[PDB]
Image (cartoon, rainbow over all chains, first blue to last red; front, top):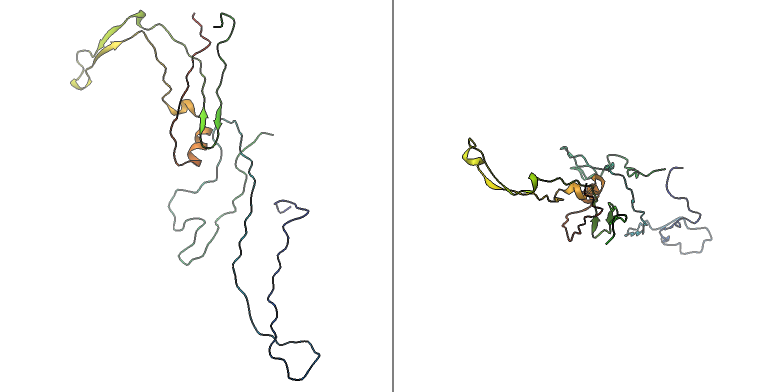
Length: 103
Length: 104
């Protein structure tokens, strides 16, 4: 109901954690669990590749159709772009429904 | 190769997009009159025309077909598909037909 595709078997969850690295144990045995750990974090790179199937528009209508377009008028910032501070923003919620079809 | 009661052609108006190329076809109905009584006549600018506007020539009984405007070959929606999706286009080949002729 928010949108998208309902999948019985959706893309699986990818789970990740940093393996615990203990700090130095005491020199005499203690059966208590370790609360003492070496502070660490991890970084890396993640690639995702999806293949999408398209359904082309077959329409016979004579007149032109509504398209999603940028505005030609001048502006301080270009839409869908970084600003002077390096912040990427999205001006509007673009939807997918423009082309038309008969019932 | 037909006779009085057989059509010599069909109406093909569609456009076809193969994505490297587009093939546009247009079929229209025309009416051809008799021009200037089957005569070749010379024509020229009148007196009082400025030097810039003088001309000399010939008018002929013949007519001619001109498809040289784009909207002949493209619907406004087919034109939109072309100009929105493409960096350039050029014509490759054409095919011309006259059929279903009627002399009244």
